Picture 1 (tube, rainbow, N blue to C red):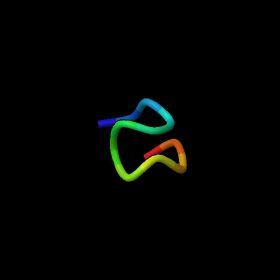
Picture 2: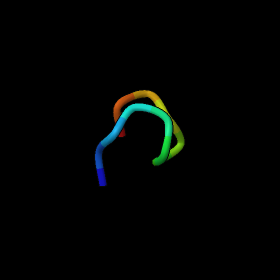
Picture 3: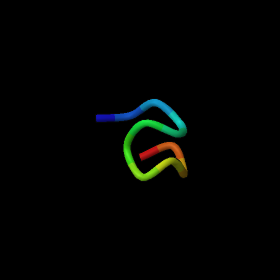
Length: 12
């Protein structure tokens, strides 16, 4: 998904 930190950060 996209979050910013959750998913290996970096707005993944």
